[PDB]
Length: 146
Ligand SMILES: Cc1cc2nc3c(=O)[nH]c(=O)nc-3n(C[C@H](O)[C@H](O)[C@H](O)COP(=O)(O)O)c2cc1C
Ligand SMILES: [Cl-]
Image (cartoon, rainbow, N blue to C red):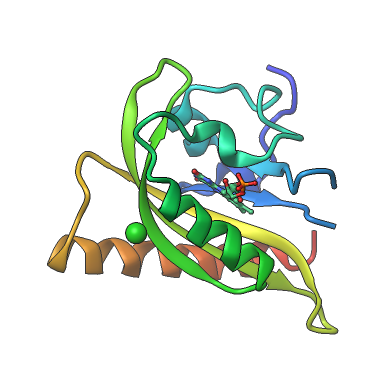
């Protein structure tokens, strides 16, 4: 397909990297697992804001939590319903955080997705957050010199 996966994009997790410094803070890198999850080609989502994953059952208060984290340049972890290309709904245990350069300025946003079948709580929530935070920290290491 168009836009061969970079080594970063073959990391075995669902994530995207956006560039705020571009119009509507769009996706510039998307992992192979993210494309498998969402059913989009890479060429179908590069240069688009991630909000295309939202649909009728997505809680809009939760979306605004993500908006406010981006605006305040800070992390957030939320759960929300997202939609594939085929309209299959999935729960997304989602973690955002900024990636900072050597001056401390936000250079990218990293978003890590753990797709599930229900809203999770208690142990499943804790283990999911452990996994997506750990993942975000390796992507912050990978993405640092892009
Ligand atoms: C790095 C990054 C990844 C994102 N990943 C998702 C995602 O997986 N699912 C989603 O519903 N929104 C995701 N978003 C949130 C939307 O892109 C957008 O910020 C949100 O819809 C709020 O902005 P809006 O009110 O203009 O839509 C992501 C945003 C960024 C910056
Ligand atoms: Cl939430």
